Image (cartoon, coloured by chain):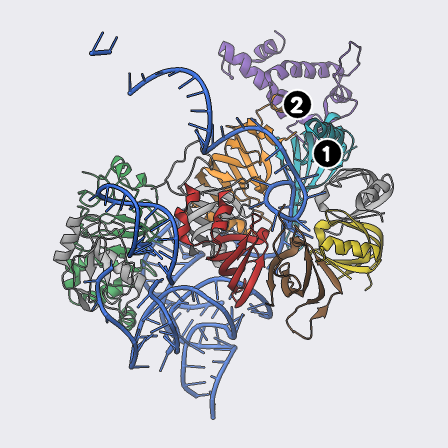
Amino acid sequence: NTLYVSQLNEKINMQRLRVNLFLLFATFGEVLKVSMNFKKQRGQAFITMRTIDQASLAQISLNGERFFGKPLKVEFSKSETKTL
Amino acid sequence: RPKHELSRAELEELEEFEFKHGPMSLINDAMVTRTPVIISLRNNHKIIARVKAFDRHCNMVLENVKELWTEKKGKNVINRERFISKLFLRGDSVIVVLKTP
Amino acid sequence: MKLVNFLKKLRNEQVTIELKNGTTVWGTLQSVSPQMNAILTDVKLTLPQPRLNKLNSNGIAMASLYLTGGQQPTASDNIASLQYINIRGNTIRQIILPDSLNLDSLLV
Amino acid sequence: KIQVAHSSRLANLIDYKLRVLTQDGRVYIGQLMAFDKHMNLVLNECIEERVPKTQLDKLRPRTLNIKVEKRVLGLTILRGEQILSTVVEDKPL
Amino acid sequence: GIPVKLLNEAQGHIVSLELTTGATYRGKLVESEDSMNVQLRDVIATEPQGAVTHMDQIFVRGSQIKFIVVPDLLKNAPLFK
Amino acid sequence: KATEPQMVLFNIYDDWLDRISSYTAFSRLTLLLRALKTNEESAKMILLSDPTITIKSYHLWPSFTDEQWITIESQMRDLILTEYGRKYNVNISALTQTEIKDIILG
Amino acid sequence: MKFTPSIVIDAPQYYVDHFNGKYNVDKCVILRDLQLETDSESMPSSLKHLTHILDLTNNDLIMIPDLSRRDDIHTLLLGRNNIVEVDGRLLPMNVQNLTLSNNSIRRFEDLQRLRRAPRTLKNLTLIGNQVCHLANYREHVLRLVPHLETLDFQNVTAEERKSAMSFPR
Amino acid sequence: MVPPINCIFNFLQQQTPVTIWLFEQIGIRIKGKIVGFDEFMNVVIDEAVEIPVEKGTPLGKILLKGDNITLITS
Amino acid sequence: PVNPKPFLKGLVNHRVGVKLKFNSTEYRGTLVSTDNYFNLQLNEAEEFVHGTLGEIFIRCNNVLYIRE
Amino acid sequence: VSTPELKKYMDKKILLNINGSRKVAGILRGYDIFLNVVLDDAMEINGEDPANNHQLGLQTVIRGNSIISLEALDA
RNA sequence: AUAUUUGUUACAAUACACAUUUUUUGGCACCCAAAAUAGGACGGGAAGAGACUUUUAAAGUGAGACGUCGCGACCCUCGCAGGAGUCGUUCUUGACUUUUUGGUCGCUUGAUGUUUCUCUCUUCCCGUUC
């Protein structure tokens, strides 16, 4: 379900970043969590989706996609999310 | 004598006395005798109203009451009159109530 | 005697609750609490226009009126229409009840 | 929008997102949880919306767009003295 | 009532206060009574016009309180069962 | 308010008879006497309709200049005109003075 | 099927989008893969329920139009929609974002539909549209957008906004 | 500890003159000799003068309501 | 050592002025009766702020002070 | 019903705001259930600290209704 | 071999109690002033000028004060875990303890609300109305 992003623009703000992420991930499926709880930034964001299929699709399509200068490294999460 | 000592009926006799003999007897005698009363609210708007009913808190039911309110801006005055057939009035707004002759 | 017990028998009647703000509420009346908390159903609540060379109305009542979410954008004058407003008792000033009902039956 | 039960008291409605009006012209929107005898109530996720003085002038009679400055304050407890009227915004999850 | 009992459940935690005078007192809640008058410890104060100061101890009258902001994790607290 | 049998004297005519001639005032009385039955509640609605009006202490009738009273008796007739009319089903235009008197007197 | 009132009523308005506002509606059985071929008709059934966000993603909609006055609505997600033109006067003061990815909007058709505004939206995504490819498309989009906070995830550069304003003058 | 109404009783029997501030809306302050009081902190003042806020006019023996009381100051 | 309530019991049917808290208006008249809350009834009152008023009822919350 | 708990405050110099405008500072003496607070050596604080400040009386009592916030400047 | 109904007890819950400084029988109200006709008004954006400010003729638009979240960065910073651990108990629950990114600086005018004082015209573009 969850997709752990990495290698993104740290210079952008938190809320804005979250919004951007939401915008990105709405095409694949219904995004349950807007932004990662830790909010460390610099790539580390967990895009929580309703469906696994949607998540998979996202992983497939947005692997190395141009988001704020740098290519985002998509990957599946190790542990399941608290909301899911 | 404080009110918390009295029993349930002694409060009823106390309220009967306060309405019959007391300040609010001005309103009570006004309700029975069908004498129109003048009421000034805090708002500053005065109603000429006949009192159908009244109560401890002074909230009262008036029928055919006429409301008189004036307003001024930079010393330019206008007098406005508003007629309502039925009124229930909450008693906290009133200040002075007089019984017309 | 508590005269609020009268209002309890006025249920399901068209009424205006005219508040301390000057805000007036036309609506169908539902159960009135012993503290005179008055709960209505289909209500059009507004503020009168003092004319007087367009003297400024209540500034707090306009904000409280737009903040009900019921004021529609295209209303020329200042009004709002909404369902289910619940009004605290101490806010009421006057209540204008309909002309049809008879008091002699209800005031007992 | 939303139709509230024709007879529904403050006890009947719980967890509905409400819209609360105070004496000062500000509004607290959020889920109601508890309330009390004197009607001071507890909102879960609440945002106070306010009307700008320039916005208030715009509201005076002549499509209007008001900029309503609002700030988010979670799990508050209001005071019955300040509350003026209450309206229903949404229905529970 | 539950609303006051939740305020008693918030003792020893950072809370926010809005007085009807317009000020804002945010700080740690030491005491609270059933009259809603509370006393707060090591509290940052915001005057109605925005000037912010700091005071170590404060006692406020409950009648003058407007809203109280309580830590969110008290939402699921057993009072609401 | 009387719990005992007694004789009490009051004047039905009050102001109107004092203002207007005696033949006409009985007629204005009879226009009223028919009417208050047809005015179940609007009587106090129409008689008090001008709130400036007050009832004199000795008198029973609302004391007034008598122009609205001519309007009051006319409105009241129309309430009698429709209530007599609706039961038999007559148009308001079909109503004539000979019918209007037959409504008044019958 | 076609976007009716019944469908709207049916739609799951329980799970609120917690990023901003409340009531993230998804029209029909599911707005994601609803297949609304015609324009978004029967918008009045929602009645401005609630930054109210509506997800229309994976649907057949040709035109971004036919809305009822929605005061709340702040977010539109329209991804995988065959949008061609989105000209309207209903949703003007309202709305803070618009996601238009993977649609059919023209570079000139998108520019024409808005007609320009002194202030509008705040977040906009036009990605995977034919128009974005078009030469000077970013400059044209910035000039059309008039006021804008974003353009396909990258903010119009302050200097770019100044140069675009000069082009407009 | 000195309860406040005890202190007021010490204003009654000690016959000390007191100045008393009213609410900020009224704009006058009263001063006189506090004689006796009730549970509601409404007090009778003998030989009281009302000063606007020293040409104020003398009042009398006057009962003053406790609702408008702000300060009672010697 | 007179307290307020016996002070009102001693001022019955005497000429008393009462200053309200608002306009600095005082009603000058013969007191009739008082309630527990110190509601006031007056006869032959006159409003000073100039007029003459037959009978008066004054609610307790609006009075500022009572004098003779 | 319940007495307010000032018990740690008494005998300590305390500032408290009377109404919207006012701020009085004095050594707290006693208090009651309505919060009526009697204190001694009262001083009315103003913008200019030494200048516009003027003492009130040897003993001053305050109606609890006009009390907004009470801060102790002290241990 | 043939879950429903009836009675009792408890809990939740609605209708009958309180006008005296801590919530519901009010410290209430007031700044004041601005459109009328028979191509025309009104709003928004951009430019010019007057009058304002600053320097010794040349530069932008009523002025001075709290905060609020933001545009840049010559900086810091590793990078995948509201939850976490323990014990009881059996395939995920309770009881007891540890405690939020942003930590900052400019703004060569972010962008924007309070509060005091004093006194706009011209041109173009876009919407509404007759």
I38 displayed left or right of K124 = right
Asked whether J64 or K27 is in front, the reply is: J64
Per the rendering, the colour in which chain G appears is green
Specify the amino acid type for callout 1.
Val
F106 displayed left or right of F85 = right
Query: Residue F70 shows which numbered tag?
Result: 2
Chain with colour cyan in the figure: B
Chain with colour red in the figure: E
The residue most toward the left is A60
Specify the amino acid type for callout 2.
Ile
Question: Which quadrant would the N terminus of chain C be assigned to in this image?
Answer: top right
- Judged by depth in the image, the label closer to the viewer, 2 or 1, is 1
Q: Residue drawn 73% across and 61% down?
A: J60
Instruction: Locate residue K119, reporting x and y percent.
Output: 58, 70
Cα gap from disc 2 to disc 1, whole angstroms: 29 Å
Q: What element does badge 2 sit on?
A: helix
Instruction: Locate residue J26, reporting x and y percent.
Output: 68, 65
Q: Which chain is disc 2 placed on?
A: F
Chain with colour blue in the figure: K
Mark 1, residue position: B37
Q: Residues within 10 Å of mark 2 (few under 14, many from 20)?
A: few
Chain with colour yellow in the figure: H
One can see residue G6 in this view: yes
Q: Residue drawn 68% across and 26% down?
A: F67
Chain with colour orange in the figure: C
Per the rendering, the colour in which chain J appears is brown
Q: What element does badge 1 sit on?
A: strand
Q: Is residue E79 above or below residue F4?
A: below
Per the rendering, the colour in which chain F appears is purple
